[PDB]
Image (cartoon, coloured by chain):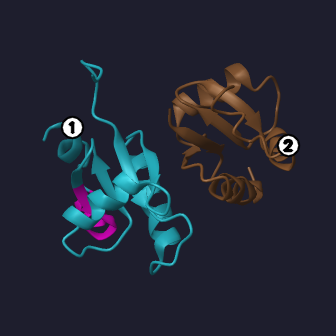
Chain colours: A brown, B cyan
């Protein structure tokens, strides 16, 4: 399943940190800009439960976590949380 | 398999970490033009998007980024070609 970093390009530098963490864990990703991407907007609004952007989404609508949660999985180094939910 | 009975998606191919000459201002200008013609789009970042990178390398003919692409690989035009066209665009994306 493809992995995305949900963002708002017009969110904050935190996107760059997220990108660095995924690359470090050899996780390929592409960006999704909620400023222009209605699918991403729908997914983030439905599932974020008020969590702030940015974040990581797998496939069409599997919200893995926002930046803070991704940070947390990374210091536990279980960021490959996102392939097993 | 792919979904039927819908419009081909439209992309602005760009490089979000810049580098390319006037990459961000030209991207911003492209965005304004597409929005002006009421054309929905998403960005493709060639820095992280390998297929978008491959598409541009194959079809750009040396044209500089950013540009507009329809579907998987229908390069409509780069920023300059798109700039000139700003008479009717809808015709070049939807009628072609």
The picture quadrant where one finds residue A48 is: top right
Give the residue furthest to the left.
B96
Q: Pick whichever, A58 or B90, lies toward us.
A: A58
Q: Residue at the spot x=62%, y=25% of the render?
A: A62
Residue B94, labelled with which disc? 1
Identify which residue, A81 or B49, lies in the foreground.
A81
Mark 1 burial class by Cα count in 10 Å: few <14, some 14-19, many 20+: few
Give the residue displayed 72% in from the left and 34% down from the top: A81
Q: Chain of mark 2?
A: A
- Give the magenta part as a residue range: B76-86
SS for callout 1: helix
For residue A65, what is the image quadrant?
A: top right
- Give the image location of residue A2, x and y in percent: 50, 37
Please, which chain is the residue tagged with disc 1 on? B
Q: Residue furthest bottom?
A: B21
Q: Position of residue B16 (x, y in %)?
A: 54, 63
Mark number, residue A68: 2
> In what quadrant of the picture does the N terminus of chain B appear?
top left
Camera-side residue of B82 and A66: A66
């Amino acid at each position: 399943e493809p992995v995305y970093i949900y963002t708002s390009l017009a969110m904050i530098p935190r996107t760059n940190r997220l990108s660095t963490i995924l690359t470090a864990n050899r996780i390929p990703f592409t960006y999704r800009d909620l400023g222009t991407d209605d699918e991403a907007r729908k997914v983030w609004k439905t599932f974020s439960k008020g969590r702030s952007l940015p974040g990581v989404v797998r496939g069409h609508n599997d919200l893995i976590g926002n930046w803070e949660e991704i940070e947390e999985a990374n210091e536990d180094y279980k960021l490959r949380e996102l392939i097993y939910d």
